[PDB]
Amino acid sequence: PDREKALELAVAQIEKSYGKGSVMRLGDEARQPISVIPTGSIALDVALGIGGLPRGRVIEIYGPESSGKTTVALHAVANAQAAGGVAAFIDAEHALDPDYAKKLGVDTDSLLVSQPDTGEQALEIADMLIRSGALDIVVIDSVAALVPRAELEGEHVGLQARLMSQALRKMTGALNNSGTTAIFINQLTTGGKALKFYASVRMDVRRVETLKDGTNAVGNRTRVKVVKNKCSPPFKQAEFDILYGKGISREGSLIDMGVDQGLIRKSGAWFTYEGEQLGQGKENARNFLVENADVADEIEKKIKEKLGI
Image (cartoon, rainbow, N blue to C red; front, side):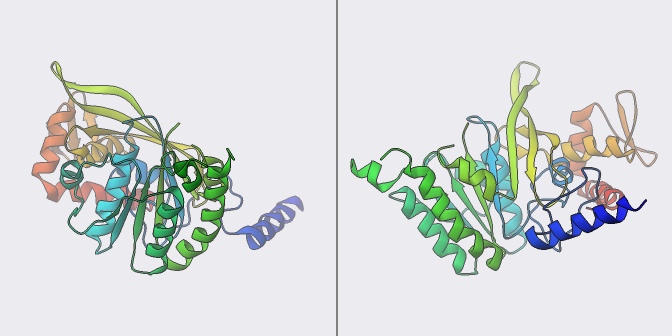
């Protein structure tokens, strides 16, 4: 009717005065950027709409201890590097395991790392790295750990939030201008009040159940909810397996997402793909796909095309 135009108008004005993702129907298809940073899971890539993390924006990944949030962050680093990018890791937790990082695909040798003296030094160094123009990604581990100088020097209570707010204001312009993505890891959030609004993507990461091989724990089924998303309709969620000592089972996400799209049929325990059989049970289907990068890439190729991601 006459209203369909008045709404298009309203939406278009909102978009003009506030930016592309300022309002969306949840049912809308995403606006696909040139490049993004894939997450490691095609499921998580689809849930984000744009097929990975956006460039030049603030990302927040939060969840409990050992929930997988860091694992997600490292894959983002790995993929950024695989595409010839440079990565930085601002570390106030001192928890990183580079062997684990390596097995995911991170080029740890090339990884820039900084273990800052204070909260403000952490963000300042990060800001210097960003304004270089030379970075594709920088990870901050973590928000809770960004303790202010005054507190560290023993000098009121509330300025960590003020620190993040100050930092993000300056940093947000540098990231947009540089095309560098900043991932902020966060626990269940000192100055996460500011981060909540500056972030273009916020991901809630959690463990759903432990994966077992008979009696020993091969890994964890992980669940991520994209609670905030300026680059595509929000509130999507995905699941994927993080295997101990290996990381996110890419092959596992291809299968799962394959059967969801009807690219991979499932006559009982037997997963099939285009008349040929992938395996009986998920682990065989998974293992088959790492042994056969050809078909795994073809399945990945097909899923993207069907969804335009």
